[PDB]
Image (cartoon, protein in one colour):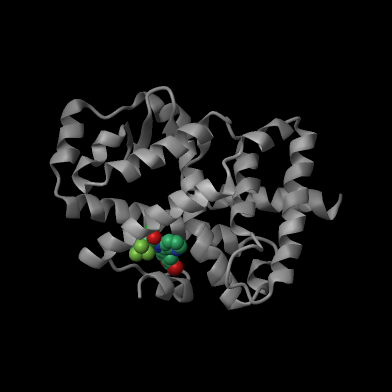
Length: 241
Ligand SMILES: O=C(O)c1cc(F)c(-c2nn(C(=O)c3c(Cl)cccc3C(F)(F)F)c3cccnc23)cc1O
């Protein structure tokens, strides 16, 4: 009935529609783990072939997040500068949070190209510290056993943050932020899940991992550029020069 319960439903609708795999598909496929021969197959690939595979999965993942953001009540109504500011700082942070759904804490593997594989699968990329940091972040997030609605509401808040440097209409973003915080806290009370609030990762940690990740992606993109058919061209122009 309330404007808030309608917001909860729409955020969860936007989320469910902008998700590539459904949680049950990822959950059932946990048994389908890459063989040592398949692992060796991936480790023996060139850095540049592994970069191409990962770059295209990450760009497709960002594209689903841009679509998620576009479907968030109020986003399209913000100025284009603000829309860029929010997506530039937050789209990859959302991708990093969404990744915990495809992560298995039991064996420390991620669902990649049809099967579950460990971080060793990525050996050829030569950025083990970064990749270990990503798996660690997914490991901490997997302990929360986040529900699909919780991930939807939390990621909307990762994106709609009025504290991002460069916002031109801070107040309009704050209004959207306040409504989403109410939606999230209202839903956690209703479901007796307010306990996750003290367990969420510190804001600086997600920011920090994201900045390290995007910085590496930028280094690879400079060395071996991939072209992408941009869903949001003004955002695309801010990262792809
Ligand atoms: O409009 C689009 O279709 C669009 C696609 C994108 F993938 C991003 C995107 N890629 N990306 C990358 O880090 C990236 C990715 Cl995901 C793959 C390779 C290189 C890059 C890096 F470094 F060159 F930009 C981002 C980081 C934050 C925020 N957005 C992005 C942005 C877009 O506007």
